Image (cartoon, coloured by chain):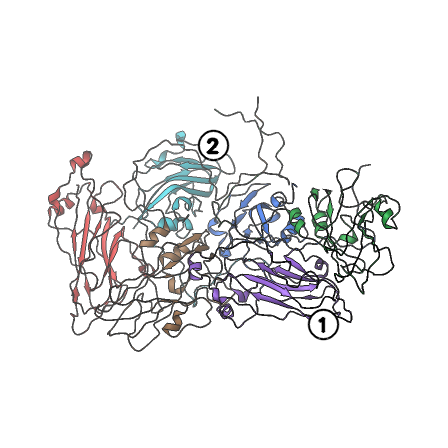
Chain colours: A cyan, B blue, C brown, D green, E red, F purple
Amino acid sequence: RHHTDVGFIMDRFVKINSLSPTHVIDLMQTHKHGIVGALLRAATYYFSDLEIVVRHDGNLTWVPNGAPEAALSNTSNPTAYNKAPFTRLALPYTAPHRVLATVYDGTTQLPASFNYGAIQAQAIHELLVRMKRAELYCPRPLLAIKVTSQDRYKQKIIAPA
Amino acid sequence: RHHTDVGFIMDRFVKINSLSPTHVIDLMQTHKHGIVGALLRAATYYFSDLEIVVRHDGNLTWVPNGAPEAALSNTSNPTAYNKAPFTRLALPYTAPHRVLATVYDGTTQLPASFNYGAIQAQAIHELLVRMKRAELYCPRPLLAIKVTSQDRYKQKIIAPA
Amino acid sequence: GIFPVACADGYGGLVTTDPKTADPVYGKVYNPPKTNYPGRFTNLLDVAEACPTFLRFDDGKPYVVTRADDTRLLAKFDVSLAAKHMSNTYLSGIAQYYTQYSGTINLHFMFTGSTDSKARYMVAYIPPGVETPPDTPEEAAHCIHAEWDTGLNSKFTFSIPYVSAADYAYTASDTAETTNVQGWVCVYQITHGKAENDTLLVSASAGKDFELRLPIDPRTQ
Amino acid sequence: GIFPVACADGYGGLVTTDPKTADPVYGKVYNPPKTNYPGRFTNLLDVAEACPTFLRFDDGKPYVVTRADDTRLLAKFDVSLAAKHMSNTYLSGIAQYYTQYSGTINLHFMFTGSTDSKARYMVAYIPPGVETPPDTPEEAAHCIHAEWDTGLNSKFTFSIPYVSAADYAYTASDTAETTNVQGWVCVYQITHGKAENDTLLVSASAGKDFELRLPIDPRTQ
Amino acid sequence: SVGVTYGYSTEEDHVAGPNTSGLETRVVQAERFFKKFLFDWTTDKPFGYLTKLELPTDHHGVFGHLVDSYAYMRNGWDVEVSAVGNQFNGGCLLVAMVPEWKAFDTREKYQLTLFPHQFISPRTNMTAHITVPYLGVNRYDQYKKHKPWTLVVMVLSPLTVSNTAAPQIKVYANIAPTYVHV
Amino acid sequence: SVGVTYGYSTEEDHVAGPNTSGLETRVVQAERFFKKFLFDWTTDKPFGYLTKLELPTDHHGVFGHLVDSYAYMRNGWDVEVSAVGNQFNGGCLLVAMVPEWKAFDTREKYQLTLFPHQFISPRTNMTAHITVPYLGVNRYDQYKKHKPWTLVVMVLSPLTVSNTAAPQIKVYANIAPTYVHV
């Protein structure tokens, strides 16, 4: 047994669909079948450090949570400047809670708490994110692909010629 | 005696003819008189680690064997991004068998097993491959160039002027 | 007094699997240590040991239709890592994100009639290629088989040895050949005692052996 | 607090012979240790010791036409590292991928007539430039020679000393001169006893000395 | 009985601690059983018939008094479920301890038993018995806005009847917090 | 005789092992010699006359029963070849133990003796005797789809005759697996 202890699984990247001149940062922003979040969604409570990568322009800049967004461009809370083409940072946890989670039933919109935060620039294209030393708590249900045809399942396989 | 123990012979490169937007990866894809495979073909069973080099564009990306090809571009199982002009990776063995081989007589098409796999991109030109720490088992027959003329053989030799 | 700048000729790709790290920035920040919190785990496998599962038949009803009469054949399913019998299955989803896998597989059985009722049943393995499913307990037995009764126990867990071609196999199945990868491994029984309506349950799970190698997305992210 | 970036001025070529390594990616993966598997080896040389070889004559028949009458001359071949006498030869192909080579060379002989038949033969070396092949055993002997009989043995292995110009030589031969590199080293015999039809076999092989330096493709890859 | 089966651990706990714990000590007399109605269960319900119960309902208890006190709090939870019948019945029901309950969907039904659980059939059990140690986002909680837990049961086998049995069965359970700190 | 000559090793082997080995133990009574026809050999065949024999043929043996059982298996192989003649013959035949046999071609003929082997001439030998220890891709095998071995012989010298000898000779051999695990 030398896998499925997250310590090796969740240290990769995953694309994110959306962007804008500002853009919230969260895990549940991930696709709900990208192999990253499946395991993530497959659990109840999880914590990690955090690493992120952005291909961009202008001046990438970031703020931790619980902050007045209205005050980012000014006075430049911490950052380093432009350099193409790869740029790689890591943020440490900041949220007001000793653990994250996936969904919080309270009388189904995601709460306003679990917030790695957001970044801002003048031009933003590509996003890479990363989970460190993570751990998970109370795994949750999980699905596979659905069965439609008869036998067992069918699927194409690569092979040389 | 300080050669012909493969540990020095099979740690070089060799061109490969074909490519396509996807492209299987195998040793027997090599030319059957390139000095690399001769020794390789000169044997029955061989194992090694593996190192590969590709001059390319776009996003080189790779998957280990026993996988649904149909799912490569999405979700980006492991990879690093573009950078010209040299790019050098190494893959560790993955095949479902404790050893490779060259040819497997079963009632002459190569089996669907021995599969370092394949890579995919949007533009692919050049290929360099490499064998690590390799070992070989039950050497097989081997030929030289054929004799046509009379004496012993004749061949041009370089020399200054 | 420069040190020889043995520059890099073409390496160092920003790529996926990498183990390289980064620089804390608004860093040097503690957190209240999260020990003593419950629900800790590491292994998809190990948590898939204590937890059993369920199955499915075309009747969409998880339990087994368990006819109780002179019939001899009970019902026959299959166990792939990906098959209609075993989709909604805590293994497969966890599985279907992999290609190499190895080790034994687990099952369960839960009885339904009142304990008084005597009973007989017979789990039985079949290798992929016997070319004919058995049709009698003793000749079924030739491959693999065992027993129990209602007597002295109601639960049970069973296992098939991890037979294969090589000491590993493909998770998904192929569209280039015919023969089933495992068979139709299922159950027989000796004379039913008495029951107006039985029922059976069945699961799978990780155990000492369920292993994997790894990994790639299949899906259409 | 930068360390002096003693940058590289023009080195570090992505080139062939290099010993530099790479970074595992989907890495950290074991394998069942492959010890105790048979057929292990390392050396093309050493495996070319226990294994003998064969030869060829214009008759395309590997064995030797072995006339058995008043004739004195048996037949004469050559031993280059690349010659019509020795193409289909486990050495040469392995050889022809090299340029420098050194050390003694091996042979073999296997008899054909019934053991009762007395016999005589005489292996004999000739240096490249005697300007005349010998035509009598004792004057042939002047270079190098030896004996055996059918008596008390049937096999034999023989060797030529690695004479050369320098303590090495070219594998392929030249198209700028005439003199054969080695000679026409071949065999004589004393009176044949009796035989309706003999036959001889002959090989070569690695031994204590067969060595090389190295390497380049010749072929038209 | 099958006896107690624990959720994730079995141990005596920390009971006295810092400022708020000093301010919100183990008020033991806040503890008392009572009974809730669960659901009905006859030969009608085919499989998949879910029935959920959010927690915790109001209650005329000292606990219930404080659960309106609308304040930072923590708690424990001890579950003991049963349904009296008679040995001629037959089937299998599923009892469930769910963290962060969400509206399920057909396919995932077949997954329930991830959670701690037991089995429900008139042969093996007659007394479910299960306890969850506390958890939550904060070190404490304030209910009204949220529910960290729920107690759910759903079909796991169709139910059988002969002439000898009772064609209807009610299902009770036992709900009372423990280890309370306010 | 020249005596036994081994293929790659000479040693008593592992016989009892893990789950499948525990499930597929050394069924010793699965072992028994028998005889196969090889080929004919007169003054006709010039050099290069190949004649191959795939392995293993069907056989009315307990071994043969299981080799249809169509299952993961392993095996051993012991070869003992001969051809009775009389001391007035003359020539040289070549016996061959081939791993992963392929259709050869003229030039490579001159290479055979890479493999383990002996010589065939009425003087030196009268009894070939050779054993291959197991190998294969898997730790085990399932035959029908594949053949890891074959037993081949081909000319190595033209054959001579006088009046005293027998103008025809048949060639037998001995084939029986050993060390069987199923």
- Does A113 appear above or below D69? above
Q: Which residue is mark 1?
A: F168
Badge 1 element: loop
Displayed quadrant of residue E66: top left
Label 2 chain ID = A
Q: Observer-nearest residue: C98 or A40?
A: C98
- Does E109 appear above or below D207? below
> Which label sits in the foreground, 1 or 2?
1
Please state if C6 lies on the left or on the right of D133 as rendered: left
Mark 1 surroundings: few (<14), some (14-19) or many (≥20) residues within 10 A: few
Q: Position of residue B2 (x, y in %)?
A: 65, 40
Q: Position of residue B131 (x, y in %)?
A: 59, 46
In the image, what residue type sits under mark 1?
Answer: Gln
Please state if B152 lies on the left or on the right of E63 as rendered: right
Label 1 chain ID = F
Q: Observer-nearest residue: E20 or B30?
A: B30
Q: Which residue is mark 2?
A: A81
Please state if A25 lies on the left or on the right of E125 as rendered: right
Task: Give the farthest residue toward the top.
Answer: C1
Mark 2 surroundings: few (<14), some (14-19) or many (≥20) residues within 10 A: few
Contact (Cβ within 8 Å) of mark 1 with mark 2: no
What is the distance, in whole Å, between disc 1 and disc 2 at their CAs? 94 Å
Q: Observer-nearest residue: E67 or B39?
A: B39
Marks 1 and 2 belong to one chain: no
Task: Give the farthest residue toward the bottom.
Answer: C70
